Length: 322
Ligand SMILES: *[C@@H](C(=O)O)[C@H](O)C(=O)N[C@@H](CC(C)C)C(=O)NCCCCNC(N)=[NH2+]
Ligand SMILES: [Ca+2]
Ligand SMILES: [Ca+2]
Image 1 (cartoon, rainbow, N blue to C red):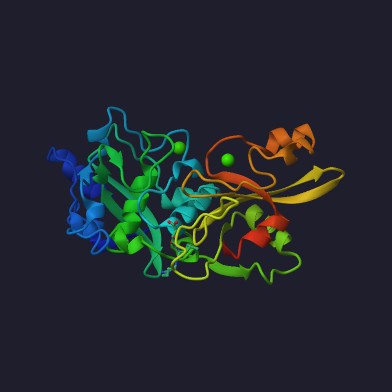
Image 2: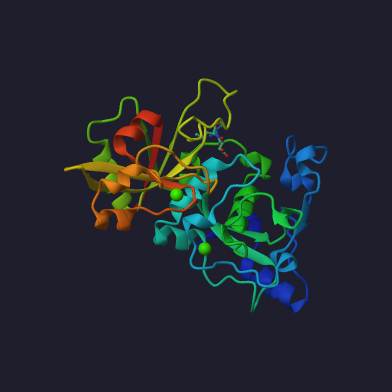
């Protein structure tokens, strides 16, 4: 029941292209440099050199919209500073209700495929349907911006494009606020917490939020804008949005420890402290908890004790829904 952004009708356009024997080309967000950017990604820029617009059906013999469900590992940041957005999309996948709204089902590259897709966002004070053609920025046959751990999966790349479309261009997405993305996917209420002055029952607040299906994100502030994308010695990225994906407690050497799980939208580069994938701490806990919580995989997701979490991170944003 969403309203058509710019008046473009997904079903009518798809049927029309199928009848006319052609693939959709978006006049509202065309496959040209103006859709990429205006400065760092403008036509006269080095970052756009070699960038060509290609459809998934031109790159692979078997492109798929969704493979093994739409999940957080499907969100791997590319050469665009839109971590705030990607962390939001990753969190979104943990609430099927909202995911199913933002990403309509029944879309594929097989039957009825006409080079057009659509998504719904909370914009201009309402739920709007945004259409996009599947021409994506590529370099040497690979996606330049967001991509999935599954090489033949494209829903996340297409959603990022629709979000870029409503904002004017991909470059417009460089630099942002996680809460802004949370609201565009939920129309809900956002709150934030200063981890340097965190409430005594903040962990409980997180537990309930995660249970209700709220979206949570966190980040580490920097002294200035020069320490951009600076990795700490503990291997955390500062000035970078992370998705908070879980909160569980474990019994460590006789007493339970509050743990928190988060994911770097890069899909790699994880924390190297206690509770990390190859950390020793997992030996001092019971097998059940270890096998049920620990996952040894370079996926950008990792656990931290809540104690270390509030010391290392500076901000936590939470978006609660209906
Ligand atoms: C994220 C990345 O891709 O690594 C990138 O650093 C980013 O978006 N940085 C943000 C902060 C994180 C989301 C904590 C940033 O530096 N924002 C300040 C941008 C100021 C304009 N902001 C908004 N929110 N419209
Ligand atoms: Ca997937
Ligand atoms: Ca991991």
